[PDB]
Length: 222
Length: 8
Length: 217
Image (cartoon, rainbow over all chains, first blue to last red):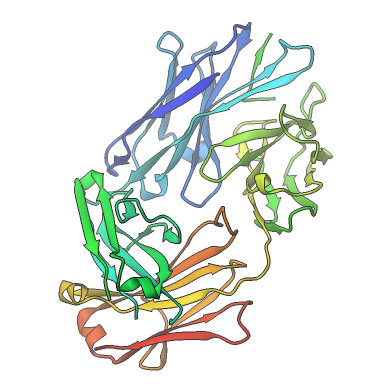
């Protein structure tokens, strides 16, 4: 209840099993029990309670919306509790959180224990790992110009983009990726600079996609 | 209440 | 399942002004022992939700007295007396009188700043992209407020619908603006079968729409 740490595979195929572990680092001693839950959040959507269990028992409560595809268990000796999900649909891509809740009567006033893990993004997709194609975005604007890089048709998330080996940060906007109908992702990163600097300064975008072990640097000039 | 523990 | 309805979906607030978020349940949240089982969470940007108010009206330690919760058995209100920048994020109500636990749909609180018109840029595809078989033409709207904006694509002067997708940044921590990308994707033969490409932007900061265009080649 001092800390919750989630772990598990970041990408799972639709026929496979989604398996997540939550490791509980406890706090000051007390008598009674905690309730541990799994909650998920699809990208840009709300929260959905998956299921949970009290620490003193071996019976699990489940959300009926989850069609009995979820199996949640715990081990206080392994200070862990687990989520298994199968079969899967693209609709199960989400950030998954583990939570611990209790009413706290140990103090002079009634209070709450309420702890959340950082969450783990799990993408369900049959797409194969693929490195991105990186194309420069060159200025087509008289006072200030804009440059960018298009990083397209990669899988899975995430990709990281820096400018001039991280030396350029002011005015940088890296847009959230969009899932294409092909099952791959594409995004753009842009930066605005004074046009007078276009002749004197070099601008390079550095793209890193570790799932495919791809690293690209593209110069963007006019 | 459901889904919440109690510590004393 | 108990249905939780939360209003509104999005709440822009000028700093210092009050905000009110409503939540309803389809059933009473009053349990046997007389407690009303309704909690409020706040999920700050890039973070996990955490508990803000519990049992309708009790503030978690560290939550300022600016936050207050009220309600009946089925109708609940979270009030923020004067909104500050640290308050931005998504608020969620949650009932726990019965399984399954259910959440409201969330209310995104953002900072209202002065109107700022977007800077508009268009990017013609590189020669590499043209040899790739598929082409992406990029339209950038830089540093604007509010979020609402219209982006229309024009091919040889004609309105083109379909084959385009948008992506928006979250509100910038430094100037409180948004930026937006609109990408038109075409087959290469289709791309080379036209001459002029343009994006037109409508936004409250512009007295009339702004058009950025290029001639292929």
